[PDB]
Image (cartoon, coloured by chain):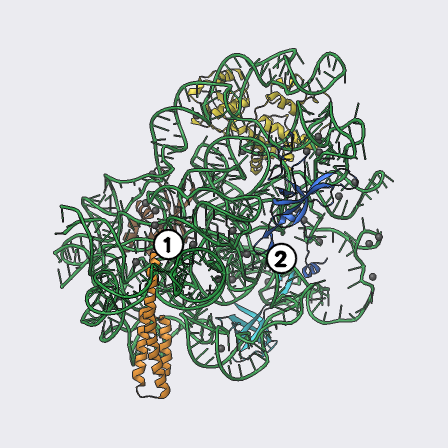
Chain colours: A blue, B brown, C orange, D yellow, E cyan, F green
RNA sequence: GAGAGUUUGAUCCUGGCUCAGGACGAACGCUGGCGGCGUGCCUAAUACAUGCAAGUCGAACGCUUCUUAAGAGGAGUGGCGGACGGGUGAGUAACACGUGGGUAACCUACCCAUCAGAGGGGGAUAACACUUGGAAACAGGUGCUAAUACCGCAUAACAGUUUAUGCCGCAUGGCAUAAGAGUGAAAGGCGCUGGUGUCGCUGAUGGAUGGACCCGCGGUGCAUUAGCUAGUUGGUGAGGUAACGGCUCACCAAGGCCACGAUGCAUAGCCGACCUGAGAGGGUGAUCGGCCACACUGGGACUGAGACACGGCCCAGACUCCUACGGGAGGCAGCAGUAGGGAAUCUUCGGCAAUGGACGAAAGUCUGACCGAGCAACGCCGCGUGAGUGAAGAAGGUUUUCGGAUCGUAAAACUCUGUUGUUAGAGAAGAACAAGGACGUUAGUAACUGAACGUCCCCUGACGGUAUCUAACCAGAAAGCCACGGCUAACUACGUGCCAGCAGCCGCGGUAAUACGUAGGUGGCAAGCGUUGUCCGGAUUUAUUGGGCGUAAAGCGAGCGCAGGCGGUUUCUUAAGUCUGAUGUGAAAGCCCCCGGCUCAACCGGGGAGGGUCAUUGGAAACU
């Protein structure tokens, strides 16, 4: 564009959007609205727990939970590690992170936090999966 | 009224002071009108750096040194100069 | 008030308001009497003019009005006279 | 944090002798681990640059954070080649000065001496191995410490002192007459690779 | 004595008595691209006798507030 | 000024996506030795138990209770303070803020300096005593009492104003002189000897300080928001204010703003600064400092130099609490702390010793400011978790091509060190002081006390027996986390069999997996490590620096054209742009440069530089 063209209509950049939107919004019980708060994690209650089929390339029974977060937004989160103790009405903590295999999972359930028990027999990468040092 | 007083500086347990002309109502470390010297009590002979001419001018304008600053100005002899200037 | 000095100031400020309102109303009545005399074309206008100026200055004393307000009123009264 | 693990394993991983004796490399000059003895694929350019960076920091027994800050200071120096200046500062580090003077056989030993405070700079105790030693500052052993077998043995054993260091045996006092020259420093290490590494 | 800002401009409204509207017509560099762009500031100046007409080049000096929007006083009329 | 992976059978180009860096008031997972310095409700401007955060003055005044007439209290009146300091940022898109000007349209207690005055009288009321009502909160009645409380009268016009001169400015006008009309004030206390010192009191002026108003320019999004305005725009008067002003009001007009974005909607405290970047820029607006705004919500004024007042008053409302049902009390966004929300943020601690602030003549009293200490690896910095010698290399683990390789000089063993740790001892600076005791010099006096200044003695530490130093003993109590298919430094065994599972992208897993789990090794870093969240970079991926539009996304179907953008040669001139100098300013702190202090560093201190599309002013005239 000419300089006059840019002056008349300046450059405008694309606006990015979060890969983990549910973590970006808080809730104000009094006003009953959603706030704009960036949170590294968020507490939610497991409304449902089960397993899901991956996308076409892969085959498994990926373990997941449908969770209503503390800001009333309902999302689907993955459950990493081998074996878990979660059930519906179990209080969990959620972190960002997609799952390539699964269609609509954008969050991970942190292990070792709140009602999520560490992974039994985990011995390498213990920080992740939330297991104490044996 | 206008004050000549010590603004504290330095670190915890290691104070330093700047002799500054400031309005009495202002916070100690807050707004001040001008810096006129420094004062380091941690030296065995307490070390003082002073703009004697500026301090005398402010005293003539009616600044009121705090107690410690008055001792400092006396030790530097500024107070006697101010007394003679009044004469 | 939760502070003893606050309670003390409540009483004293109330009393000062009583006194100040009384004196200010007195000054206004003096000015009002002179203005009405000017309107009516009375004979004691000059005596009332002196009284109005006297009242305004005495009101400036005691700090019921600012000195600038007092001078503005004096000029206004002088123009009326 | 201070590294304490085996010394030979680190030296042979780097492929050069940290102590300079070559004793570590002489026998089994393989990278540590079970795959070391057998042939290994060539290293990428990033690996080469990383290896040079590791060479310097393992030589002087420093952590990455302190190493990184020191490199930045070297950059601030205006005159002379950047990598050369960085190596000069590495030398001026207090531990290395003790090592060069030969009051300790190894840099670990010199560091422990400084940490325990047996050394004094200009007659003043200094327990900071990281301490920066200027040209002309006199590094000496604490008077109480002078009669300990370790430092005395190290002095008698060390027979070659770099030109830039000046040392007195009886007083056990040394100092850098001048900043070390590039060739006086370790030549096997290539400072340009380290410079480019931190350029990232 | 300190000086008040005086501006040159062109009258654009005289339908109000004892006052005129002037336009300064400056240019400013665009912050990003730096081209000079025409910028128009207009002032309401008090006219003592409605001398100045529309489309007249006049000078105005800043003054104390004379009305809600007046802040300037007419000085000269250089072109009609 | 570093790139890399991924479209294909393969290739080049285009293009998006993803990664390698840094940062944080972070949180979470595992782990966890210490010290220095700093930081710690980002969410509910949600509600708040409890304790404290604003008092002081007896040398303004009159009372009242005790100690053998003392000192110590107790409540009055009166003075100053309470408008500072501390908290939060809700609101606010606005001269709120930033920067630079203007005010001849301004005010200012306490502090300095100058010139004057400081005379005469008077009536009160608290307190007190009784006494009415009330459940309480608290209101009343009667009778006394003082003041530096209150009111008159006297004198003061230098204030303001008019006039007349002289000078000057930027229109209104400013300054000085003279004259003139009308009126305006005050308080005494302590102490020397009627005089007098000192602190007070009154008027005028000037200074400093603080505040106030106006103005140029600068910094959010949305036009799938285009009309807005009726005291609105201006005038004439009048009133009001510290002051200009539609600030308000009566008349007179119909004007004012707006595509150079009005208005409306949404979001937001602004800045110095901070993070990133090669830079241009992008993001942020914690801690620290400046300004602004707010104090349960809404409104109002009173006192005052100063408030429309966080810990003041009045009214209304929501909520909490007390009632004897008549009526009352309250406001943590002060310091701690509690509940609640949340992923998530601390002790209901010590002291006024230092610096600062209020009152006092001063001792001193008050100060949750502020000094410290406490808790959190939350961050940065610093030091350890030993050092030296030590085998063709012990056992065991792992792995074997069964020979052997690797963990590995690592261990063991021997010789040394105590940073730390434990134990004992010794031990700061931070303290200047004020008052008080002595003298001495100035000015003033007749003389003194006394004032200002000067020199000695005396006097005080919460931190705290804290830092630190010395000496004895012991390798003894003190290393984890993640990663190892490529990007990417780091590889083999089992177990598993498109399962269990991994994953940032490519993608791994279907019985021989360096990609899953475990193991052994190895790499990275280290009292941290990693994950998530968010910002910048890489991203030339909005390209001003720095991209494109024949076929990859992209030339309107074409023209006529208002505004706008741009514009042929040349003489002279101008100096808006442009270049350049000087001056002023762009606070302090923080970056950056020198120089110092902490054993180093972090940190702290000193001196510089920088930082503006800045204002004033002087130059140049090529280009616009
Ligand atoms: K009082
Ligand atoms: K592919
Ligand atoms: K690509
Ligand atoms: K006050
Ligand atoms: K401005
Ligand atoms: K008007
Ligand atoms: K705000
Ligand atoms: K309000
Ligand atoms: K208050
Ligand atoms: K104090
Ligand atoms: K108190
Ligand atoms: K003191
Ligand atoms: K991998
Ligand atoms: K371009
Ligand atoms: K075409
Ligand atoms: K020009
Ligand atoms: Mg893994
Ligand atoms: Mg001292
Ligand atoms: Mg560290
Ligand atoms: Mg808050
Ligand atoms: Mg807000
Ligand atoms: Mg009085
Ligand atoms: Mg860039
Ligand atoms: Mg409060
Ligand atoms: Mg010790
Ligand atoms: Mg590799
Ligand atoms: Mg694996
Ligand atoms: Mg870019
Ligand atoms: Mg096509
Ligand atoms: Mg096409």
- Quote the CA–CA distance across marks 1 and 2: 43 Å
Ligand 24 falls in quadrant: bottom left
Quarter holding the N terminus of chain C is bottom left
Q: Is mark 1 within 8 Å of ligand 4?
A: no
Residue at image mark 1: B24
Q: Is residue F71 above or below residue C38?
A: above
Task: Locate residue A27, reporting x and y percent.
Answer: 60, 52
Q: Residue at x 37, y 54 (%)?
A: B24
Looking at the picture, tell me which residue is in the foreground, F170 or F574.
F170
Which label sits in the foreground, 1 or 2? 1
- Chain bearing mark 1: B
Quarter holding the C terminus of chain C is bottom left
Residue at image mark 2: E31
- Asked if residue A44 can be seen in this view, the reply is yes
The quarter of the picture where residue F162 lies is bottom left
F300 vs F221, left or right, is: left
- Chain bearing mark 2: E
Q: Is residue F485 above or below residue B81?
A: above
Is disc 2 placed on a helix, strand or loop? loop
Q: Is residue A11 above or below residue D165?
A: below
């Amino acid at each position: 564009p000419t300089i006059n063209q840019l002056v008349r209509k300046p450059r405008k950049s694309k606006v990015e959007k979060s890969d983990s939107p549910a973590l970006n919004k808080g809730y104000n019980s009094f006003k009953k609205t959603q706030t704009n708060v960036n949170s590294p994690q968020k507490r939610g209650v497991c409304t449902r727990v089960g397993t899901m089929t991956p996308k076409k390339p892969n085959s498994a029974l990926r373990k997941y939970a449908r969770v209503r977060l503390s800001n009333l937004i309902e999302v689907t989160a993955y459950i990493p590690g081998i074996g878990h103790n979660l059930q519906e009405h179990s209080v969990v903590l959620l972190r960002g992170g997609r799952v390539k295999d699964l269609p609509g999972v954008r969050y991970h359930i942190v292990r070792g936090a709140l009602d999520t028990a560490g992974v039994n027999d985990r011995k390498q990468s213990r920080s992740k999966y939330g297991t104490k040092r044996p | 009224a206008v004050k000549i007083r010590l603004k504290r500086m330095g670190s915890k347990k290691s104070p330093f002071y700047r002799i500054v002309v400031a309005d009495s109502r202002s916070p100690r470390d807050g707004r001040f009108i001008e810096t006129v010297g420094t004062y380091n009590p941690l030296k065995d002979p307490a070390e003082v750096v002073l703009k004697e001419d500026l301090v005398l001018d402010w005293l003539s304008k009616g600044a009121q040194p705090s107690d410690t600053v008055r001792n400092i100005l006396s030790k530097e002899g500024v107070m006697k100069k101010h007394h003679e200037a009044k004469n | 008030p939760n502070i003893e000095s606050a309670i003390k100031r409540v009483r004293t400020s109330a009393n000062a308001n009583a006194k100040n309102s009384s004196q200010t109303n007195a000054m206004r009545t003096a000015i009002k009497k002179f203005e009405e005399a000017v309107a009516a074309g009375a004979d004691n206008v000059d005596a009332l003019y002196n009284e109005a100026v006297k009242a305004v200055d005495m009101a400036a004393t005691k700090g019921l009005i600012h000195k600038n307000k007092a001078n503005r009123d004096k000029i206004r009264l002088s123009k009326l006279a | 944090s201070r590294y304490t693990g085996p010394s030979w394993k680190v030296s042979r991983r780097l492929g050069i002798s940290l102590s300079g004796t070559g004793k570590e490399l002489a026998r089994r000059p393989y990278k540590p681990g079970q795959h070391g003895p057998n042939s290994r694929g060539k290293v990428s350019e990033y690996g080469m640059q990383l290896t040079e960076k590791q060479k310097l920091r393992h030589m002087y027994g420093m952590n990455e954070r302190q190493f990184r800050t020191l490199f930045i200071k070297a950059s601030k120096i205006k005159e002379g080649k950047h990598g050369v200046n960085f190596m000069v500062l590495l030398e001026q580090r207090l531990d290395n000065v003790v090592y060069r003077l030969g009051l300790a056989t190894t840099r670990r030993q010199a560091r422990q001496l400084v940490n325990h405070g047996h050394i004094t700079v200009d007659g003043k105790r200094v327990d900071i191995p990281s301490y920066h030693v200027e040209v002309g500052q006199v590094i000496g052993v604490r008077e109480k410490s002078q009669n300990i077998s370790t430092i005395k043995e190290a002095v008698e054993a060390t027979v070659g002192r770099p030109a830039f260091v000046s040392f007195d045996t009886e007083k056990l006092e040394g100092s850098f007459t001048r900043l070390p020259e590039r060739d006086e420093l370790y030549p096997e290490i290539d400072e340009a690779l380290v410079v480019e590494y931190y350029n990232q | 004595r300190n000086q008040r800002k005086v501006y040159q401009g062109r009258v654009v409204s005289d339908k109000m008595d004892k006052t005129i509207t002037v336009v300064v017509e400056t240019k400013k560099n665009h912050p990003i691209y730096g081209k000079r762009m025409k910028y128009s500031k207009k002032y309401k100046a008090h006219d003592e006798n409605n001398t100045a007409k529309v489309g007249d080049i006049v000078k105005i000096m800043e003054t104390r507030p004379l009305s809600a929007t007046k802040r300037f006083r007419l000085l000269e009329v250089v072109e009609e």
